[PDB]
Amino acid sequence: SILDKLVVLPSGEYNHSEAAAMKQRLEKIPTSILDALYSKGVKIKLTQGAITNEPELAYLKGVVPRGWEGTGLTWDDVPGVSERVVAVRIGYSEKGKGHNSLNLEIHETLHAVDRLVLNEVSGTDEFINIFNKEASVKYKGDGYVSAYPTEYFAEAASLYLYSDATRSDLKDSMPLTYEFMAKLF
Ligand SMILES: [Zn+2]
């Protein structure tokens, strides 16, 4: 599997079974897309501590994420991020673990796929049209998935890839998004 080289586990001590479970869920992403991620120098780092403990993310320590002034939140509290590295904290996959995604590792990986593999497909007129019609169905008022096409892309692709139940739910609730995802994957 491409995941044996794309997924970087900690060199120190880590929760073995949880890291394996996350690695297994990343297999829901098509192999061709994972291959393409690796060719762009992308690494999916599963971290045992705060993502900011990673040398390349240490610069974010004590910095306030945009939109969060006056809340006491810093990047140290954020369980996952996606830039040229995808960093996800081990044990924080489920909704409510410091984020509101269906699955943290799939969600954050799909941002890197959008940016570095698919030429920002979330920003195309076709996807914008879909986002304007359907992002409101499940996410109205969240100022996040319903506010940014990149977020709707990552979360709606997560619904598509995670399980058969979440995909069926997407097909019924957001049919234009389901059609776009099926054509893409
Ligand atoms: Zn996101």
Image (cartoon, rainbow, N blue to C red):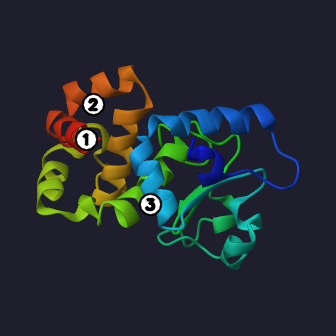
First reached walking from the N terminus: tag 3 or tag 2: 3
Asked if the residue at label 2 sits under 8 Å from ligand 1, the reply is: no
The single residue placed furthest to the bottom in the displayed view is 59
First reached walking from the N terminus: tag 1 or tag 3: 3
In the displayed structure image, the side of residue 78 where residue 175 appears, left or right: left
In the displayed structure image, the side of residue 142 where residue 171 appears, left or right: left
Q: Residues within 10 Å of mark 2 (few under 14, many from 20)?
A: many
Residue 150 sits in quarter: bottom left
Residue wearing tag 3: 112
Q: In the image, what residue occupies the spot 70% across and 44% down?
A: 90
Question: How far apart in space, not on screen, are marks 3 and 2 (Cα)?
Answer: 22 Å
Residue wearing tag 1: 181
Q: Is residue 118 above or below residue 159?
A: below
Give the foreground label among 1 and 2. 1
**Amino acid carrying mark 1 in the image:** Met
Q: Nearer the viewer, residue 122 or 62?
A: 122
Residue wearing tag 2: 170
Tell whether label 3 touches label 1 (CB within 8 Å).
Answer: no
Q: Residues within 10 Å of mark 1 (few under 14, many from 20)?
A: many
Q: Nearer the viewer, residue 97 or 156?
A: 156
Asked whether residue 29 is in view, the answer is yes
**Amino acid carrying mark 2 in the image:** Leu
Whole-percent x, y for residue 84 in the image: 52, 69
Provide the secondary structure element on which disc 3 rests: helix
Provide the secondary structure element on which disc 2 rests: helix
Total number of numbered discs in the rendering: 3
Q: Residues within 10 Å of mark 3 (few under 14, many from 20)?
A: many
Q: In the image, what residue occupies the spot 60% across and 73% down?
A: 64
First reached walking from the N terminus: tag 1 or tag 2: 2
Tell whether label 2 touches label 1 (CB within 8 Å).
Answer: yes
Question: Can you say which quadrant of the picture contains the C terminus?
Answer: top left
Q: In the image, what residue occupies the spot 17% across and 63% down?
A: 124
